[PDB]
Length: 297
Length: 294
Image (cartoon, rainbow over all chains, first blue to last red; front, side, top):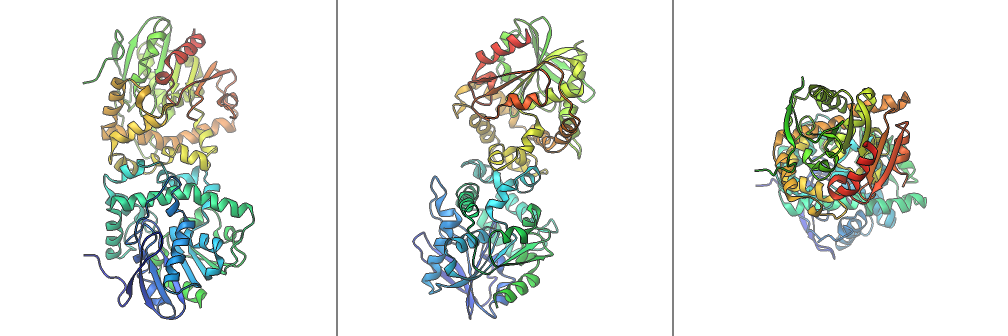
């Protein structure tokens, strides 16, 4: 009952040491991996990936634990869902396809994998784009009253299991739809393809999937922050040429001026706002696709 | 089917212009008011009120909108559940008993009503005791990563309705038990009387009550913070003799130094317990309150 929103794209089931990664694969040219975030799946790129497919081999992957990717059993430290472990697992999956050097564009949680990848193994990346994020360290370092009210879910979803899992299970549909709507500029679901929202709703209806996402946020509050902290305090900068895009109405711009934060984190950053809320590829598919094609070409 | 945990205490329904305040009343002597917090009701004082009622007229009130007290209708600013509004209504309720100058002890949210009452109408209080709180402004000012994870519920329950209400309905029984357990020293429900836990549980099972609690935390994020800010910037201090009690577990730049910035006359001591002083450590808490109030 779930629509195929990537006409002409293949489907790959990439085995890795930490489980299978699902990905839609299309186009030809240089390899470009697209990583979605929360609470979405690979299908968030359905509006932009066709345009990228004109110039690149596009691989649109579900994150470890998300969508149709396998769910590694987490542990005390939320290890498989730290961005470092996620980045290592997606490298391994790109090596299965023979992509040892690729371009990466990530949104939300996938953008956090992406820059962590760029910090842990910058030689895997030719170029990198991150959409509407600042580093995890920066969100926490700027977590005052105003921001803690805005991204309350960073602290709520990071609470010990099973507190958020138990509250989310009463009406999953409400929460996933509330988070999709409230982060768009319009405040509703009008920007999303109804068929895309079905993918997101169904992925959220699974209790194991919701636990994974909380594990993702638990890693975000702890190991991900700690991994970021060591780098920023060591002056570890991303040497990969990168683009930072953010929505004028999105999450990253509320914390600080995004381009100036990223210049502290990478030696070669260009940045551009996009008139859109958090979900740049769906709210602003034309503007996002053009900014990505230009940067990666 | 709830237990009477105040044997001999009367049961009073106190009228105010914003709704009825429920209270257990016992003992005799000077008037002493006891205010509970989240997610509890007046019954949380059931272990120390008997010791206080040996010295005082003990008025154990459900906060406005909490327990069996009436739930006034909120507004866009959550006005009735701002600590300034709850203090004014509790002043009114005490006036209905002829109590215009009384002692006040508060825990958690009831402690925020209390210091706000001490700031707004200091002449109403002979002495003031806050249990395991700092001023709301200090919480938000200190908001960082550690604090956001620790009192996550301060931002979660402050989200616009119906987001917290909807999610609290996902499992209200678990959530109130979780809050009760997580904030103790023991980390479980062993510190609480099961008959008292039943009171907290059945109160939390009412969605209107849960909405009230969200309005309290929405106030705590906005109007209450703004009210506190004016007093910080104006250097206003509580002139009432103050006792600050806190659990050494469950929150060191000490609450004393912080409360010294808000009060001119403040004593303080830690109690070996978690967040719930009167139930985890009734003897230590009752003793401290008696020495201070008597």
